[PDB]
Amino acid sequence: KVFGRCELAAAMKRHGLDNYRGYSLGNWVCAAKFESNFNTQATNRNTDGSTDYGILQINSRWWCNDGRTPGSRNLCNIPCSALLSSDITASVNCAKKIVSDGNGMNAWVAWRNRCKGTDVQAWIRGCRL
Ligand SMILES: [Cl-]
Ligand SMILES: [Cl-]
Ligand SMILES: [Cl-]
Ligand SMILES: [Cl-]
Ligand SMILES: [Kr]
Ligand code: NA
């Protein structure tokens, strides 16, 4: 499913991401934009054999099982496929564990290269929230 901007914002808020671990709603929306263009079905294979899945491009090396990432962990205890659903619940639940890990949203390369230090409030400006 391909979310619209405010739609996703609303969905993320509902799921508790606004200011989660101090990251305001517009960081999550910005990260989703550039990670997956808001497409729950996005997948990208990495050089190490791992794969990133879903709207927040969560990686199979640590967070989900895809049966093809040898020696990987499944810290969110979930099939990577769950992450591709049009219901963002699984991605959100897993994202909270990742941003709680230790380096916050820096875990999302697109986020620190394209969102961090920018006016991320602009991603929700306009939305009925
Ligand atoms: Cl914001
Ligand atoms: Cl695996
Ligand atoms: Cl949803
Ligand atoms: Cl942080
Ligand atoms: Kr998400
Ligand atoms: Na894994």
Image (cartoon, rainbow, N blue to C red):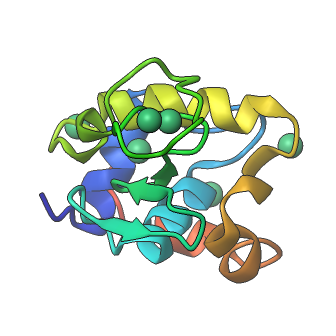
The picture places residue 97, in percent across and down from the top left corner, at: 64, 26
- Indicate the quadrant where residue 15 lies: top left
- Name the image quarter holding residue 71: top right
Is residue 51 or residue 22 the one in the foreground?
Answer: 51
Residue 100, by quadrant, is top right
Q: Is residue 54 left or right of residue 56?
A: left
Q: Is residue 126 visible?
A: no
**Relative image position of residue 33 (x, y in whole percent):** 43, 72
Q: Tell which residue pokes out farthest to the top in this image.
A: 77
Q: Is residue 124 above or below residue 91?
A: below
Ligand 1 falls in which quarter?
Answer: bottom right
Residue at image coords 66%, 48%: 24
State the image coordinates of residue 82 (x, y, percent, origin top left): 25, 33
- The residue positioned 79% from the left and 58% from the top of the image is 106
Q: Quadrant of the N terminus?
A: bottom left
Instruction: Give the residue drawn at x 74%, y 80%.
Output: 113
Q: Could you tell whether 119 is left or right of 64 in the image? A: right
Q: Nearer the viewer, residue 78 or 50?
A: 50
**Image position of 95 with respect to 93: above or below:** below
Between 110 and 119, the one nearer to me in the picture: 110
Q: Position of residue 80 (x, y in %)?
A: 33, 38
Q: In the rendered image, which quarter contains the C terminus?
A: top left
Q: 30 or 107, which is in the foreground? A: 107
Q: How many marks?
A: 0
With 94 as the anchor, is 66 left or right in this view?
left
55 left or right, relative to 24: left
Can you see residue 80?
yes
